[PDB]
Image 1: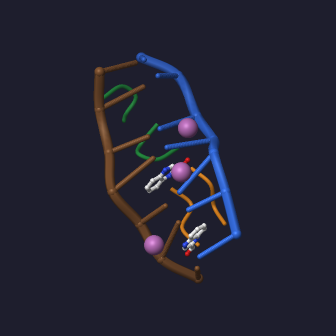
Image 2: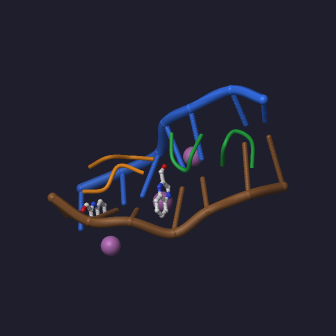
Length: 10
Length: 8
DNA sequence: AGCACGT
DNA sequence: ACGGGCT
Ligand SMILES: *C(=O)c1cnc2ccccc2n1
Ligand SMILES: *C(=O)c1cnc2ccccc2n1
Ligand SMILES: [Co+2]
Ligand SMILES: [Co+2]
Ligand SMILES: [Co+2]
């Protein structure tokens, strides 16, 4: 995720 | 068809 | 550690 | 038919 907690996605 | 990690 | 997608 | 991307 995020970052943090890429995206999703990317 | 989707590209969320592969995008086929 | 943290995330499910459709042409 | 297919696996990506940093705080
Ligand atoms: C894209 O729409 C799509 C749907 N199903 C799949 C299954 C397996 C590989 C790629 C796929 N892409
Ligand atoms: C991308 O690398 C990837 C891997 N697994 C998945 C599962 C479900 C939806 C999307 C996905 N993308
Ligand atoms: Co599907
Ligand atoms: Co897979
Ligand atoms: Co991966």
